[PDB]
Amino acid sequence: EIGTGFPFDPHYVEVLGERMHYVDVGPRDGTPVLFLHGNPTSSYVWRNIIPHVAPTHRCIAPDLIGMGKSDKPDLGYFFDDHVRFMDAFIEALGLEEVVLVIHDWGSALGFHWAKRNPERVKGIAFMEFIRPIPTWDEWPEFARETFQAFRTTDVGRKLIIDQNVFIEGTLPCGVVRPLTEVEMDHYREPFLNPVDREPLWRFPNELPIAGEPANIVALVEEYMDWLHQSPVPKLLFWGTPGVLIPPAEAARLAKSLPNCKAVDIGPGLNLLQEDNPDLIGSEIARWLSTL
Ligand SMILES: [Cl-]
C-alpha cells in the first residue's frame, strides 16, 4: 500500500511578496536535504520518500510558486519566475550547504542553482530530469502530438487551462501503477480554479525540445556541461521505459557523469516516486550516509 496521506504540518515563508508553502521535518541540525518537485506536482510527490530520510536528516520540500499550497499571483510563470522565487526561498530559509533531491522541472531548478552555487551543493539525487531534447523523434506519436498541441496559445491553452488535461490526462500517464482518486484529489487541489492553471501550461512551453525556446535550451546546456565536469556526488534513479530519461540515456549518464551512482527502480515513466518510493527513499538515506 503506497500511502496516500500528506501528514506534514504546513510551513510558510514570504518570498518576493508571495507566500511559499513548504514541508520541514527531521532534525534541525546537520546538512539539510532539499526536495524540488516539477510539473504538475507538488511536495505531495515526495510524501513517501521523505520518511526514509527524515529519521536522520532535515527534509525541506517547497511547493513552487503558483503550485501546491503556495500563493498564486498573476504571473506568466516562466522558468525565470520560478528561478527567482526558488533562489529567494533558499536564502529566506538561510540554507548554506544543501543536498538536492530533484525531479522534472524541479531538476532544472536544482541543476541551475547548483551550477551557480557549486560550493554549497554536497550531493544531488535526481530522476527523470530536464535535458535538451534534440528532436521530437525521441517521443511516440501520442506524446508528440499532445505536447506539440500544448505549445500553442490557442489549442494548448484550451487543453491545459480550460479542459485541465495536464492534471486529468498527462499526469496519470506519467505513472505505471494506477493512481487512486484520493491521490488525484491531492494533485487536483491547487488547480480547482482554471485561472490558476497558468503554470501547468507555461511549463511545457518552456521544455527544451528541438532547439526551442532557445534561451531554455542554452540554460539547460549550461548546467548539463557543469554537471559533466563537477565531482559533486550524484545519485541517478531511472526506470523502464522512462520518459525524459530512457534506459540508454540513464546508462550514458551513469558512466559519463563524475561520481555518479545509478539505481534501477524497475518499472517507471516520469513520476518515479509514485512507482517505487521505498527503493528511492531507502537508497537516498543509504547514499546520504556515505557523503
Ligand atoms: Cl512540463
Image (tube, rainbow, N blue to C red):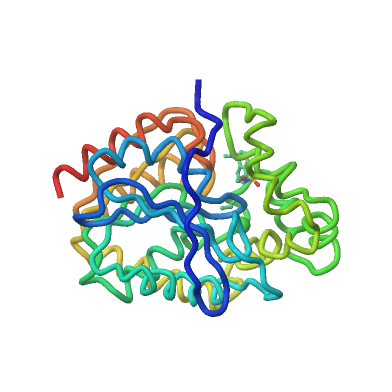
Left or right of residue 140: residue 157 = right
Depth check, front residue: 140 or 54: 54
Residue at the image point whose x is 67% and y is 53% from the top: 190
Residue at the image point whose x is 44% and y is 58% from the top: 107
Q: Is residue 38 above or below residue 54?
A: below
Left or right of residue 103: residue 281 = left
Q: Residue extending furthest left?
A: 290
Residue 250 x/y as whole percent: 38, 45
Residue 139 x/y as whole percent: 61, 48
Within the image, what quadrant is residue 116 found in? bottom left
Left or right of residue 194: residue 225 = left
Residue 49 x/y as whole percent: 40, 38
Q: Is residue 243 above or below residue 206?
A: above
Q: Is residue 234 above or below residue 114?
A: above
Depth check, front residue: 43 or 25: 25
